[PDB]
Image: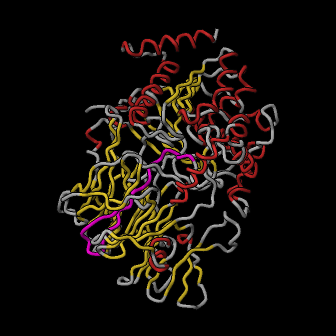
Amino acid sequence: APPVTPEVLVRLADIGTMSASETTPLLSLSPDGRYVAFQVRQADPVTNLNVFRMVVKATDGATDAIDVDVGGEYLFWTIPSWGYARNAPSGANLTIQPRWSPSGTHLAYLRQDQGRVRVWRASVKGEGASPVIEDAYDIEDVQWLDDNTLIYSGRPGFVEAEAEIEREGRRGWVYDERFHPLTGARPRVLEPISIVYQVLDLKTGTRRAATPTEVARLREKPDPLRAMVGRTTFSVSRTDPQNINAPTTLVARRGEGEPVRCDEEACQNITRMWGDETANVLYFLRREGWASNEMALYRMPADALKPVRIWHATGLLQGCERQAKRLICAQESALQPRRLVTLNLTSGQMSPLYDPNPDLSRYRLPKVERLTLRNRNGIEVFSDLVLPPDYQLGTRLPLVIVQYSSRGFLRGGTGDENPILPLATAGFAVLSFHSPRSEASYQRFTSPIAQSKAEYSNWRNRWNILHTLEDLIDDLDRRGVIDPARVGLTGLADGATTVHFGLINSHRFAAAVTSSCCTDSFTASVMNGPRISGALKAYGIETDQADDGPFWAATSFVVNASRLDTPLLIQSADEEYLGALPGFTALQQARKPVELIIYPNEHHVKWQPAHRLAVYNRTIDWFRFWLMDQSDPAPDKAAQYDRWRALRALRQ
Amino acid sequence: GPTPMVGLDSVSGQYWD
């Protein structure tokens, strides 16, 4: 049975944005409940393109899925942040939620071609799709008002503001709060920029202004934490509404009556609920078990406050919507990539509905085992241990750590950068680390910004993270599973920070890979520009200290270059590389084994399939080289190993 | 991180959760 290689992993299809959870709106049920519509994305590293398909599948399971549209460009998820109308893209794709017409015969949805987001309309038995709305601005959302009428939104003001920036540039721009140098040398558009609503009649091609009523049908979103059954409104609240770390509890109000709080433990920290008038019940989801490692679904007769658990598992259920007494969900788990599933709301039985991948038991899969421990600060931790398919007990393996969430399918860790199953296939033990809760998250805080400030104070939470990794390593060391002198560490985003912290404040790692650098004043103050730099200070990032200040000594590679002896590979997007340069240069000057790779037209999370594959392969090669002393003799890698042999020789 | 909600994804202006 063939192995799971980087070539296999990069081609495993997906549904919705990279990191999806309970409320990710990645599917839509038809009005009568008989069909589910959703987008499938599949990456091709040879053509270096994602291929997108809009898919319709009967919820009864009896007929094959149908592609009702094929095509489009990778549409970035973007939002306003920091007072900018559009922050740099994280690189993640926007989840595309198809809108069914009231008749159930057509879909409307966003789709990008030639750099422009339009509304497309597709026939649901497969007969074709075409764009029906385009404007000077990207369309941001759409709904059906009736079978022939669409309302849609976007920001022509954003376009106009861009043209004003372009005019102003003729006189030079003052460097101020509009700039974010890391990502580009132009002023950004500042908020406020308004959203404009328009209505299109598809039968006449005419457009008109929306009415306030129509507008609210687009603007208002359902609260997934609120439901009605009869006269009873279910919601969730805290005994102390200000304290964000106080657990929420299910509450019931009959009409305008007093709220009644459910006392049961099961009613705490609900993530999703659904009311069913016919059955007169409330259903809800939540996380539970050690370190919240499992999901569970509850059924609660709406007369009372006695929830009963009907399903629980490791994994995730995402985007779930109800048809009668089934839930239709996306679902994933360690060895199951994202697929659609039906959950029986009486028995709690889960059945396959649609899997865009073949069955992976076709491949020789690594062995997975969920680890649990309480860390030295008393906090419950889980993580996943992945072992090579031919693992014989007694064998001490090199270890590679991938961060920092492990709830779902073991793909590439956060940002999909570090290939878990292929690493195991290559002979490594892999720890898929699920970063634990901070101490601060157990204390009273009125703002997530104030909590952050407590976590960064003296890098207290970063130490809790590092000590947790050291606990896990020590565990696997006692079990005789790993050689503790041969531990590799990877990170992207918050995991990158952990890598930087880890290489300076321990000697437990023999090799590392990061997607970005650095955690230093240059990156956080200078390259962010004055707006973001100033805003980060409230989060506990000391951007008013220069790099030789006390806060940065724990993480700056410029300050600590001369004692940083661990081999480090940085595989950066061009959009983040500038931040790495002072650090990189100090390391080279101090003759350390560091290498920086740059990828063009990329983001914080990488989107181009050829790039991802190349990242996967180099990261495997890197760990094989430093932790196994092995090199692949393929002649197109010879120059890479020349370079890495030279890095190795610097160490003496 | 990929998902732009609550907390810091590193120190360069991206959000987590």
A264 relative to A14, above or below: below
Helix, strand or loop: magenta stretch: loop
Q: In this orientation, does residue A389 appear?
A: yes
Q: Which residues are magenta?
A: A88-108
A211 relative to A474, above or below: below
Q: In this orientation, does residue B17 appear?
A: no
- Image spot of residue A11 (x, y percent): 33, 39
Residue A94 inside the magenta-drawn segment = yes
* Quadrant including the N terminus of chain A: top left
Foreground pick, A491 / A471: A491
A162 relative to A575, above or below: below
Residue A257 in the figure: left or right of residue A451? left
The number of discs equals 0
* Residue at the spot 53% in from the left edge and 90% down from the top edge: A255
- Image spot of residue A296 (x, y percent): 45, 63
Residue A497 inside the magenta-drawn segment = no
Residue A499 in the figure: left or right of residue A624? right
- Image spot of residue A269 (x, y percent): 56, 66
* Residue at the spot 44% in from the left edge and 70% down from the top edge: A298
- Image spot of residue A241 (x, y percent): 68, 72
* Quadrant including the C terminus of chain A: top right
Foreground pick, A178 / A584: A178
> Which quadrant of the view contains residue A354?
bottom left
> Which quadrant of the view contains residue A56?
bottom left
- How did the renderer colour the structure? secondary structure
